[PDB]
Amino acid sequence: GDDRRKKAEVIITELLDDLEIDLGNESLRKVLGSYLKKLKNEGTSVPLVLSRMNIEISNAIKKDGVSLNENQSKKLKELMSIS
């Protein structure tokens, strides 16, 4: 019953599709995009990859000061909540 990887990838895909390509959130889309490939290609565990990502989304979210709407931050929190 473990589909944390599939679940994590789904949330990122959804998030990226929603974020919109713009100068404002390029750094965030970058991290998101980067971890989506790490999830599919790296032999690492979901908790290890996401713990490292959790950190990354931090200094990127406040970089350009990405202003995420309620729905997006909840999608993000729901991502970290996986592990």
Image: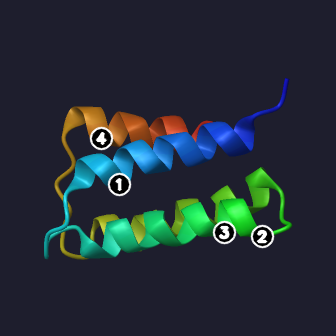
What's the CA distance linking mark 4 and mark 1?
A: 10 Å
Residue 83 in view of the camera: no
The residue to which callout 4 is attached is 72
Q: Are marks 2 and 1 in contact (CB under 8 Å)?
A: no
User: How many residues crowd around disc 1 within 10 Å: few (fewer than 14), some, or many (20 or more)?
Assistant: some
Earlier residue among tags 2 and 1: 1
Asked if residue 65 is positioned above or below residue 19 in the image, the reply reads below
User: How many residues crowd around disc 2 within 10 Å: few (fewer than 14), some, or many (20 or more)?
Assistant: few
Q: What element does badge 1 sit on?
A: helix
The residue to which callout 2 is attached is 42
- Of 75 and 65, the residue lying toward us: 75
Q: What element does badge 2 sit on?
A: loop
Residue 2 shown left or right of residue 25 in the figure: right
Earlier residue among tags 2 and 4: 2
Residue 73, horizontal then vertical, whole percent: 33, 41
- Of 77 and 41, the residue lying toward us: 41
Residue 67, horizontal then vertical, whole percent: 16, 54
The residue to which callout 1 is attached is 16
The residue to which callout 3 is attached is 38
Q: What element does badge 4 sit on?
A: helix
Residue type at mark 1: give it: Leu
Q: Which image quadrant: the C terminus?
A: top right
- Name the residue at 39% across, 74% down: 30
Residue type at mark 2: give it: Glu
Residue type at mark 3: give it: Lys
User: How many residues crowd around disc 3 within 10 Å: few (fewer than 14), some, or many (20 or more)?
Assistant: some
Earlier residue among tags 3 and 1: 1
From the image, state whether disc 2 or disc 4 is nearer to you: 2
